[PDB]
Image: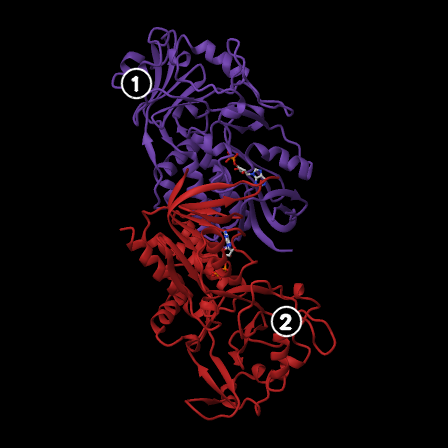
Chain colours: A red, B purple
Amino acid sequence: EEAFDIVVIGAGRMGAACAFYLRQLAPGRSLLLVEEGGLPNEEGATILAPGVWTAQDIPAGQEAQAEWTREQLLGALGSGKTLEVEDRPLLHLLPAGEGSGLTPTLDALADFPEALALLDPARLPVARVDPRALTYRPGSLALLAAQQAIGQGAGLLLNTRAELVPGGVRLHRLTVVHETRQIRAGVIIVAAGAAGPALVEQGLGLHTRHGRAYRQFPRLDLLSGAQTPVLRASGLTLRPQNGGYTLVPAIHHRDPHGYHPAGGSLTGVPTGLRRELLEDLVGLMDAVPALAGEGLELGRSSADVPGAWLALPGGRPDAPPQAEELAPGLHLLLGGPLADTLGLAAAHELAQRVSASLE
Amino acid sequence: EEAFDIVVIGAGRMGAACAFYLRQLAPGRSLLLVEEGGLPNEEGATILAPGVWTAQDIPAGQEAQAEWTREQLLGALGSGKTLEVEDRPLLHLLPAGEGSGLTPTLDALADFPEALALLDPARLPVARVDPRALTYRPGSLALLAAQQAIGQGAGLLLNTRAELVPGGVRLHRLTVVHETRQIRAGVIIVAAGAAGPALVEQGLGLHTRHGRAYRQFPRLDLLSGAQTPVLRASGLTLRPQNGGYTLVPAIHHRDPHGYHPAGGSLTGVPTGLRRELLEDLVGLMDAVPALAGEGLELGRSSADVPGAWLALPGGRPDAPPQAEELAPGLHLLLGGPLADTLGLAAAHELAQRVSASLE
Ligand SMILES: Nc1ncnc2c1ncn2[C@@H]1O[C@H](COP(=O)(O)OP(=O)(O)O)[C@@H](O)[C@H]1O
Ligand SMILES: Nc1ncnc2c1ncn2[C@@H]1O[C@H](COP(=O)(O)OP(=O)(O)O)[C@@H](O)[C@H]1O
């Protein structure tokens, strides 16, 4: 039936960015953007991502991708548009102070008292400061990218679930009855986030080693400022936002295929946080007293706690964003836990390659 | 709950254009575009509209609106974008030749033989030529407008039915279960096309005299060119397109509230055309033999024939596009049978007024 040169599945930060770069790299190549949710999609990972760009999230060898992504952020993708991005130093609080060029927490939080009251200076005396860290809303980044892509002639299909079939895509909708509709495509970019691996598996039998982890983002209602630095401890992050802090748990491991997030087992009372997060908090309460006061919103059940599924490339919690061609014309785009520092770069790199194999 | 300064209901040619002009006139005023179909929507009137701009469709006093709309068309709304628009003269074939500055069909179709074989020069000797007529695809116009509006920060909501409530809008969706969601709005533009009058009636008890007519656009598979002029006879139009002609029936009157298009009663055989169109054809077959040959696609039932509902302002088949504020902050935007010559103008006029009352 109808056909497109390029079909991008997924309108989150990754797919939206990739569709944008492809519209500027290959404007003569028709592109269709398919998203099963809306635009934006508050049921996705991109919306809850803390949006922290930090030199501490750059794996060895990825300095080029990290800086290019940073430049894009401050330049709003070079679209003459507005993208709220503030300069906010990031501190990696540490116990026994001894090693590389660290900084005494006492001095680091000199003009930031609202961040001091959260911890215990004695149990976290030193830190690794990153003066170039930045904060932004991934949701705004993604929307901006989608908008610009659409303003550039990108086909748009929302509230549509894409299914991969040999040669093209099958689109499912709802009018009440289903509406299946196939379409040919020369190139298909799978930017379904954490759902990307399964998509290609159940659709084309293409096996991968990628995994997925469910991460919650409970809020900490304690005084915060527009310039109060991002803080990290034992892998946990305190992202100042909306006058408070958003707690970004560490991912210790991938979650199994058959797993339903439940959480709730704190000192004899059922909460909305997973057992693992609960344990982490208990282990950080002394160092970060704020985790033991009235600030943290624990909720009653997992339903009251903001959460999302993030892809884990290769199943590694610390693996960066990446792309790969699993078959002729078929690419799998993965963002992941480091997408805030390396996300755009991986979408642009994929766009360049796709654009070339078309010229 | 959540609120917007401006909410535009309907993403067809009218709503899409209005949302575009509002984004440029009042960029600082948030705007949400709601459409129950997709983008584009091939289930709307805009998609089937012949897109004919002709000085013969300008009612007295509407010359300013007509020319402004024409300028927008050739300039693609001034968006530096591409909008296919060709120069195509329009001929209003007439019987007894005698009156204003007419032109002998024989000379008018001098270099256009493929248009001559459709009629009988004797029964239609003279015509009223319009050298400034233009043809374009309303669908492309609308999409372009929506795209540009989105690239300008216009909120977008598709596959969502809007319902007017005191103060704001109620949004219905489908995930399988319904999802009602209200939103406050300072200004609400009702660009639901033919469904606009009922919308406000069943939602706010606001009575109007506007009507609706169902018009079909059967195709005539006979030789056509990129420069073959648009032809009209006894109110019927032959719009050259895709190597053929699209038949644009005349609207003699409005269709009643409880009316289901059926059609099909030609010389003892059931077809897909309404009785009225059938009669018109019979009355034009002599003058336009092409209507009696193998060219016309009659179909078996109305389901096989391209059709759409068009609003009739004031219930008058020949009334132009218009807007009105039926209540504080509530506007009803109507396109209609003359939207190809006056549509943009009415959407821009409404945008200016809405923008001013906000400033
Ligand atoms: N099979 C599917 N068909 C269409 N769209 C999909 C499908 N599965 C997921 N999506 C969309 O893919 C998008 C990616 O969002 P997200 O998880 O944030 O990706 P990422 O974080 O990698 O940018 C999601 O927003 C989701 O709405
Ligand atoms: N109540 C509704 N809620 C949301 N969208 C609507 C509703 N009713 C109609 N629409 C949309 O309003 C749009 C107008 O399309 P159209 O009929 O071509 O308007 P017009 O011809 O005046 O530009 C339609 O495309 C339709 O999809």
| Apparent side of residue B331 relative to residue A74 in the rendered image (left or right) | right
Q: Is residue B175 above or below residue A256?
A: above
Q: Position of residue B40 (x, y in %)?
A: 47, 40
Q: At label 1, which amino acid type do we have?
A: Glu
The residue under the point 36% across, 72% down is A62
Q: How many marks?
A: 2
Q: Residues within 10 Å of mark 1 (few under 14, many from 20)?
A: some
Q: CA distance from mark 1 to mark 2?
A: 75 Å
Mark 2 vs ligand 1: CB below 8 Å: no
Q: Is residue B131 above or below residue B195?
A: above
Q: Is residue B182 above or below residue A300?
A: above
Q: Quadrant of ligand 2?
A: top right
Please identify the residue farthest to the left as the structure is shown.
Answer: B111
Q: Quadrant of residue B294?
A: top left
Where does the N terminus of chain B fall, quadrant-wise? bottom right
Of marks 1 and 2, the one in the foreground: 2
Residue A195 circle label: none
Q: Circle 1 sits on which residue?
A: B114
Q: Residue under mark 2: which chain is it in?
A: A
Q: Position of residue B210 (x, y in %)?
A: 60, 28
Q: Position of residue B333 (x, y in %)?
A: 54, 36
Q: Is A243 in front, or is A44?
A: A44
Residue A274 circle label: 2
Q: At label 2, which amino acid type do we have?
A: Arg
Q: Is A338 in front, or is B258?
A: A338
| Apparent side of residue A10 relative to residue B133 in the rendered image (left or right) | right
Q: Is residue A222 above or below residue B233?
A: below
Q: Position of residue A93 (x, y in %)?
A: 51, 85
Q: Residues within 10 Å of mark 2 (few under 14, many from 20)?
A: some
Q: Secondary structure at mark 2?
A: loop
Q: Secondary structure at mark 1?
A: helix
The residue under the point 44% across, 50% down is A33
